[PDB]
Image (cartoon, coloured by chain):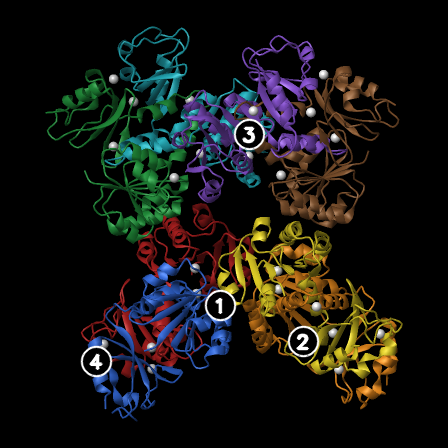
Chain colours: A cyan, B green, C purple, D brown, E red, F blue, G yellow, H orange
Amino acid sequence: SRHVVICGWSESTLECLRELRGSEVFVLAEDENVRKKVLRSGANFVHGDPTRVSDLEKANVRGARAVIVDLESDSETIHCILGIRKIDESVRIIAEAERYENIEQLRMAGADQVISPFVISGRLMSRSIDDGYEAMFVQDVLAEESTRRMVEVPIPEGSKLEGVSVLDADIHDVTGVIIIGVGRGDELIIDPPRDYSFRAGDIILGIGKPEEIERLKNYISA
Amino acid sequence: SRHVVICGWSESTLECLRELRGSEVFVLAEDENVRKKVLRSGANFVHGDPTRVSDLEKANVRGARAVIVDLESDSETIHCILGIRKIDESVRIIAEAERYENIEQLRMAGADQVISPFVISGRLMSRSIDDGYEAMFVQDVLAEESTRRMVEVPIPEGSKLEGVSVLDADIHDVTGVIIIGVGRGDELIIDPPRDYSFRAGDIILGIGKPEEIERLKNYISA
Amino acid sequence: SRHVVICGWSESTLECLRELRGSEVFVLAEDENVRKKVLRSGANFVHGDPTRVSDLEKANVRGARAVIVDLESDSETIHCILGIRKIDESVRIIAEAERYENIEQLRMAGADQVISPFVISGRLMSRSIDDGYEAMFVQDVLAEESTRRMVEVPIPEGSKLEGVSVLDADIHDVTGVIIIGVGRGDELIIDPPRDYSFRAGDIILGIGKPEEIERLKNYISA
Amino acid sequence: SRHVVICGWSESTLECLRELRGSEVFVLAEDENVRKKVLRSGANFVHGDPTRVSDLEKANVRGARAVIVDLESDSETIHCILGIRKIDESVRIIAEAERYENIEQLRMAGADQVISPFVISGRLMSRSIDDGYEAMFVQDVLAEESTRRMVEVPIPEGSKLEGVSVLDADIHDVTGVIIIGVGRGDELIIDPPRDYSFRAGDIILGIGKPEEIERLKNYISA
Amino acid sequence: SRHVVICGWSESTLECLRELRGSEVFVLAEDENVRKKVLRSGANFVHGDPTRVSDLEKANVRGARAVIVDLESDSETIHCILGIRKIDESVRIIAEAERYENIEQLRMAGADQVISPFVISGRLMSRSIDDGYEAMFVQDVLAEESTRRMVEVPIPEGSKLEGVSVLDADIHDVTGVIIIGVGRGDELIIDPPRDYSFRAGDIILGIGKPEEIERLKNYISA
Amino acid sequence: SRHVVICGWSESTLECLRELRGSEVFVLAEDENVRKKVLRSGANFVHGDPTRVSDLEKANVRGARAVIVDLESDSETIHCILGIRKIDESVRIIAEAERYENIEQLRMAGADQVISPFVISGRLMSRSIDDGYEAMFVQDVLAEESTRRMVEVPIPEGSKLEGVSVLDADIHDVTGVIIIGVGRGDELIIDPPRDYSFRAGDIILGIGKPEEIERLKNYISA
Amino acid sequence: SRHVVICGWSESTLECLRELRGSEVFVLAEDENVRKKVLRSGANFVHGDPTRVSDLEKANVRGARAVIVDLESDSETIHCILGIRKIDESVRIIAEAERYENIEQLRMAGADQVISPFVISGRLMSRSIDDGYEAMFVQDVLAEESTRRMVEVPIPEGSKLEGVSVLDADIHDVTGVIIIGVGRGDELIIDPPRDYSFRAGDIILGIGKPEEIERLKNYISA
Amino acid sequence: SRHVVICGWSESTLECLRELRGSEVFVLAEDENVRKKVLRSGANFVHGDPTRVSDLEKANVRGARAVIVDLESDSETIHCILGIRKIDESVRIIAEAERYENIEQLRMAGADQVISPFVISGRLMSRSIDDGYEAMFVQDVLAEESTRRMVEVPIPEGSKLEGVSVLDADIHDVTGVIIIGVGRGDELIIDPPRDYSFRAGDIILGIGKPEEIERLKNYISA
Ligand SMILES: [Ca+2]
Ligand SMILES: [Ca+2]
Ligand SMILES: [Ca+2]
Ligand SMILES: [Ca+2]
Ligand SMILES: [Ca+2]
Ligand SMILES: [Ca+2]
Ligand SMILES: [Ca+2]
Ligand SMILES: [Ca+2]
Ligand SMILES: [Ca+2]
Ligand SMILES: [Ca+2]
Ligand SMILES: [Ca+2]
Ligand SMILES: [Ca+2]
Ligand SMILES: [Ca+2]
Ligand SMILES: [Ca+2]
Ligand SMILES: [Ca+2]
Ligand SMILES: [Ca+2]
Ligand SMILES: [Ca+2]
Ligand SMILES: [Ca+2]
Ligand SMILES: [Ca+2]
Ligand SMILES: [Ca+2]
Ligand SMILES: [Ca+2]
Ligand SMILES: [Ca+2]
Ligand SMILES: [Ca+2]
Ligand SMILES: [Ca+2]
C-alpha cells in the first residue's frame, strides 16, 4: 500500500515502528542523532521540523495513508495536526494525548483518532489494586505472541447475515469467536443488544484463536 | 480499606488519583512544588525521596495495601521497588515500565503487576492505520462513565456453577454478560475453551450493563 | 475599565507593561524567578501554566477586556489561544507570531490581532540598505515622547462630516492632521480615494501635533 | 550594486533574505546545519564566528554595501559591530537590538541604524487593546502585496520644487501621494510645518498608489 | 578456567585488572575512549551499555566465571545485576556499593558479594586518629609485595583434621600460620571458639609466611 | 581531647563522621548546600576553600589533634596537605588517595596515614572470584557491631611481659586474643616471629571478644 | 583624591585592591557571595550588573577618577565600557583583554589603557626557555617591596632641563637613575636618542633607589 | 635544539606557542577537540592527563629542554610539577601561578621559574590610574614589533671587560644600550651599583636598537 509518515521519535512510535515492519515508513524528527536508530528499525529518516508546513510537505504527507503524530508536548501535537490538515484534508491522523484535557482540542484540530497512554495507564493502575486481570487482559490481547487474537472481520456485500439479529445469529455458539463489539463508521457498540440487526459494511470486533477466525470468515461469507 | 502509597508524581498518577476517590492516598515525591496539586486531588503529601528507605517508612509503606511506583527512569523504579521489598515483603506493588525490555527486570525486582503504557500505545497506534475500533474498545471499557463495564465477579464457595463447565453454563444467553476470561491466582485464561470447568475461587472477567452484572451475581449465588 | 491578562513573560510583554501605566494587569507565567520584575512594573503576578485551562480560569480571563498572548513558541501561543477561546468566546485576544506561516493559524485559532515582530523587523532591515527613513518613521511615531502622535479619532453619531467625501471635507488644511486611513470595523482603508464618503461610526487614523488633534476633534463634532 | 553580508541567522534575517531576492548575499553564522537553508533562500553561506575579524574578512565585508548584524545577544552584536568598524569604517551597518536600553550603545559602537523589533511589538500590543488600526497600518504598508506603498523619492537638482514651501507646493492635491515625512541626511521631519522650504537633496517619504507615484516622480522633475 | 566480565570502568576495576593479569578479561563500558586503556591493561574491550541485556550478551556473560559490576550509581548497578540474573542465574556477581544503605538491596538484586569501599575507608579514617595500625594491617596483607599473605586452604576429604577441635588441633604452634577465620558455604566464623570441630569442606583463612603455608598444606592432607 | 578538622565532604567523610560520635568535629567544605547534612551528624560547619591557607586558619588547624583530608581529586588533596603543613608542622594528617601512583606523593607532602579505598576495593574484588572470605573478614572486623573486635592494647611501662618473647608469653591460650601484629612507632610487624621479644611501649594489634580483651589487659598489667 | 570604581571581581582586581590601600573603592559585581572578600579588602560592595547603566550609576561612575573593567568575557567588557561611556565620557577606563585580538576593539570602545595579561605571560614564558632574567625584571620592578622603584617623575614648568637635550643632561651619571623612557601625553618613547630635547610637561620613566629618585626630583627643579 | 613540552592549553600557552615557532613543541592536554588548533599552531598534540606520570612520560619529558606548565588550577599545576620532578630532576619547569599565595609552593615543588599574570596585571592596573606609562613600557618592550628590543647578552670568557667596574665601563655612553640589570646564576641585580665588578659568565640585560646590540656585542668581545 501507500507509505506512512511518523512525526516525532519516542517510545510509542518505536513500538509502532516495531509492529509496522514491511511497510514504507518515513520518520520526521529534529534530532540528527536518531538517524541510526530509525535506520536500524528499518525506516527512512527525514531531517526536519514536524510543525513546519515546508518540512511536513517534504516528508510527502499528501500521498500517505496515515500520519502518526507523537511530539514532545500537546501544543506541538496540535500545531503539527493543524499543519497536516492545512496540507491534506483527507489523510488519516493518529495522535497521542499527554493530558486528558486536550483530547477534545486534538479531535477538533483534525485528528482522526486520539490515544491517551497516561489515561489508560492511570485507569489500569487504579484498577489493579485488588487484582490485575484487566491489565493482564489488555496487555495480552494486544500482543502478537499469545493464542487469542483480537481482529476486525468486515461484513461483505450480499452475505448470509444481512439483516439478521444477534440472537438468531449465534456467532459464539457456531464459530467460537467472542463478539465483544460491532462497529459502524466512526462509532463502536460494545456488547451489542439482542435486537441489533446486522447491516452490510459492518465491522465485527472479536477475540478468538485463528481457526475460529477462519470458521467465522467462512460463516459470514457471501 | 487501608491506605495507598504513591511513589513519584506524573500524569499516570494524576489519572490514578482521579479514579481513587474514596480512599486514603499518601504521595511521596521529591519536588516540593507538587504539594498544591497533590492536596487539591484529595491526597496527603509526604516530601522525600522514594528510593530512600527512611522516606519510604515516612509514607507508611508497612500498613498500606498497595504501592504504586511511577518514577522518572526504570533504574529508579527498580531501586524503589527493592526499597519497598526491604520494608514490607508481602505488600502489593504496581509498577510502570518506561521501556519494553525492563519488564522482566521489574518483575524480578518484586513488582506484582507491571503496566507498560508505551507498548500499549504503540500497539494501539499501529492497529489503527486501517480502522480504530480496537483503540476505541480499550479506551471505552476502562472509563467509568460509559454503559458497559469490565468487572471481576468472583465465584463464591458453595456456588451453583462449581464443577459446571462453561459450555454447560452458557452465561451470555442467560445473564447477558460476555465472559471474555476466567482467572485464578496469577494466571488468566482469555477466551476459555468449552471443556473448562469452574471452581470455587475463580474470578470471572466480563463486560455488561450493571443490570446484567447484578443478574450474573445472582446467577452464581447459592 | 476592566483588567488585562498577559500570558507569558518576554521583552514584548515587558514593553507592553511599560506603556500600560494606570491599568490593572495580571501576568500569568510559569517561571517563579520573574515575580519581582512583574511586581516592579505595577502588575499582579499569577503563577501557572498558560496553556492549561485551569490556570487560565485562575487569572480571570472572563472579566478581562483584552488578553495578550506571547509565549516561547508559536505552538504554545496557538494552544493558549485555543484555551482562552474555550472559556470566553467574545474576549479580545492579541497574539504574537514568531513565524510568517503561523499568522493565519493564529487567526483561525481565534486571535483578533496578530502582531509579527520578526516580519516587521526583516522588512525594515531590507528597506534600510540605501537610506532608512521608513524605520525612523515607524520607530518615531510609536514612541509616546515625540512631537507628532498617531491617534484614532472616532466619528460621533450626528457629526457634521456625515456624507461628506474626503475631498470635500479637506481635513489637512483645516486641522493639520495627516489622514493616512479610515477604519470601519475590522477593515482599514489606507490612503482613501477622494470619492470615499464618511459615515458616523468611522475611525480616522491620523498623525498630528496635539493642538491639531484637538482642532480636529472640535472640527468633526456635532 | 555590491553584495550584502548578514551576520547571524534568525527569523529577522530569514524574512530579510526573503525580501532581498535577486541580489548577492553572504550569510556568516556559526552553525554548519543552516547551510541548506541559506542556499534554499538563495544566498551563499560562510561558516565562521561573526565576532571574529578573520571570519568577517572571509565573508567579504570590505566590498559590501551593507552589513546586517543580528546575533544572539547585544554583547555579541556590539562585538561584531566593532569588528566591522575595525575592517571598514565606511560601510553601512544595520543592527538589531534585543533589549531597549542597548540602543544608544549600539549606536555608539558604530551602527548606522538600530531596529528594535520587540519595542515596536510591545507598543503595537499596547495600542491594540482598544482597536488595532496602528498594527494594521504598519503591517499593511510594509507588506509588498497591498495597493499603497511607502516609498521614497529624491528631489533632483534644479527642480521646480526647490525653495518652495509645502503650503505653496500642495503635493497631495495635485499628485495624490500623502506626504508623511521629508528628511535630510540622517534626520527625518515627520509632518513638516507649512514654513518648511524644500531644498535639493531631500528625500520625500510618501504613501500612495503607483500611478500617483509616477505622477509624483513626473511632477518633481528638474 | 573461563573468562571474567567487568561492567564499567573506574579505579576499582583498574586495580582489579592489575591484579587479574594472565586471565581473559572482557570490559563492557559506554565510553569508546577507554579502549586503549583496556587493551594496555591486557583486556578485551566491548563497547555498549552495561544495563542492557543485548550488550551484556555481546560481552559473553553466559560462559563467565565471575562478573564484576562497578557502575556510576547504585541504581545502574542494581539494573545491571538484574540484567545478568536474567541472562545467567548461576554466575557469580561481585558488586560495589557507592552508599552504605544500598548494600542489602544490592544483595536482594542478586549480588553474590558486595564490596563497599567508602565504608571501609571511613572506618579506617576514623580508627586512624590515635594510631593507624589497622589501615597498615589491611593495606599490608592485601598488597602482594610483603612477606605475610592472607590465603585460604580447603580441608580435603578424609583429612587428619576432620572432626577435631581447634584447641586439640593447635595449628599455630605446629604450622606457624595464624588462624583468623574458618568458614563454610557463604558464612565465616572469625576467631572460632575452642569447641568448634572441623569438618570436610571448610575453608581456613590464615596469615603466614609461604614456608608456613606449605607446612599447613602438608599438615592438613588426607 | 581536642577537636578534629575534616576537609571536604564525601562518602568517606560521612562514614568517618558517623563513627566519631562524642567528639568535636569541624567540617571545612566549599559547598553551602551541605550545611544541613553536616549539622545533622553533630559537626559544626565552616564554609571555605580547603586548599586556601586562610580558610585553613579559620577552622583552627593548630589546636586540632587530627586533620582528615578527603577532597574531590588527588591534586586538591596534595595542595591541602601542603597548606596544612605550612601552618602546623606537627599535626596528624590522614589523607585519602584516589590513585595508586599518588600514595608516595601524598606521603612526601606530609600525610601521616594515607588510606587508598580504590586499591583495597580492587584487591578485594580480584580476591572474590573464587570465594570471598577475605572481603567478609575485612568488612566484618571493622564494623563496630559484630562479636569480634580489632583493638590496640599498649604495653605500659613496667609490664610483666617486658623481655618475654611471643613464644614464651603464649597470649592466645591465656587470653584468647589473636595476635596478628606488634607495632612500635610507625612500624607494624604482622605475624611476628617467635624470637621477637616484647618491650614496654609496644602496641599489640589483636582480635578477640571483649571479655578476652579485658583478660588480656589484666594479663599484661604491671 | 576621588574614588575608584571596579567593575567585576577576579584575581586581577584582588591584587589591584591590595595595592589600592588609602583610596576609596566601590566594587560592582553580580555575585552576592563576594561581599565578604570585598569588605575584608577595604572596599565598598555594590550589588548589580556592570553592563547595566542603572547599576553603573549606583556605583558612582560620574564622580570617579578611574574605572577598572575586568569582566568574564571581552564581549561583556566592551558592553560595560560603552555603558560607562554613556554616563561619563571623560572618565579614565582601564580595561583588561582576555584575548589578543580584542585589544583594538577595546580601544575603539573607549578604554584609555588596555592591559592584556595573557600576552605578557606568554611572552615571558617563551623568553624563559634559556634563562629568565626578563621575567624576573618585570616581576621585580612592579612589586613595591624591593630596592629599585619604577617611577614617573614629571618635568615641571620653569625647569633647569627645559630645552636641554638628553645627551647634554646625562642624568644617570649625575643622579643615578636609569632614564628608560620619556613620555608626553599618550605617546611613550622608550630609549630616546641623544638628539631628543626635553620640554615642560614631559614625564620621565626611570628606575632607581628612592634616594636617587629624590636626587632626580631635586635635579630637575628650578 | 631539543624539544619543548607544554602541559595544558590556554591563552598564555597559545601566545607562548606563537612566539616558539620553528622549535619542536609537544602539547599534552585532556581535551580531544583542541587537536585542530594545536596542529594549526604548528605543534604536535599528545592526548593525555598531564598530572599522570605515565602520560607525562609519553610526551617525552626526559629529553625536553623546558616544560611549560599551565593547567586549570594551582593544585593541578603543583601536582604536574611534582610528577615532572619525579620523572626528571634536571629539566627546566616554567609554571604559571593563578594565586599569589601559591608562588612559594610552586617554587618548593620544583619549578625553575614561576610567572604570575594576575599579580602583574593587578599591579599594572593599580599603577595605570594616574597615567599608564609602565604598562606601555612593559607591553611594548615585550613585543617583537617595536624598534627597541630587550635582550640578554652574555659575557664571554677572556673578554675586555673582565674585572672592570660599571663606572669605568660606560656601556650606555659607548654602545647606546641601556643596561637595566646584570644577572648571575638564578639571581638578578636591577640597577647595579657603581662598584659592581664584572665577572666572566655574567648576563647583561639591556634595551636598545639592534645596531646598538651589535656594537655592544663587538665591544664586550674576547
Ligand atoms: Ca508521547
Ligand atoms: Ca481488579
Ligand atoms: Ca473461542
Ligand atoms: Ca512515567
Ligand atoms: Ca485495525
Ligand atoms: Ca450484554
Ligand atoms: Ca515573543
Ligand atoms: Ca529606504
Ligand atoms: Ca501638521
Ligand atoms: Ca535576534
Ligand atoms: Ca488603538
Ligand atoms: Ca492617494
Ligand atoms: Ca565506583
Ligand atoms: Ca587506632
Ligand atoms: Ca607465623
Ligand atoms: Ca574521596
Ligand atoms: Ca578468595
Ligand atoms: Ca577467642
Ligand atoms: Ca579576567
Ligand atoms: Ca631569555
Ligand atoms: Ca642607580
Ligand atoms: Ca593560566
Ligand atoms: Ca603611572
Ligand atoms: Ca640606546
Which residue bears the numbered disc 4?
F214
The answer for which chain carries disc 2 is G
Residue type marked 4: Glu
State which quarter of the image contains the N terminus of chain H: bottom right
Element carrying mark 3 = helix
Q: Callout 4: few (<14), some (14-19), or many (20+) C-alpha neighbours within 10 Å? A: some
Question: To which quarter of the image does residue A181 belong?
Answer: top left
Residue type marked 3: Met
| Dot in front, 1 or 3 | 3
The answer for which chain carries disc 3 is D
- Would residue G200 appear left or right of F152 to someone viewing this image? right
Which residue bears the numbered disc 3?
D125
Which residue bears the numbered disc 1?
F99
- Asked if badge 3 and badge 4 are on a common chain, one would say no
- Asked if badge 4 and badge 2 are on a common chain, one would say no
Residue type marked 1: Arg
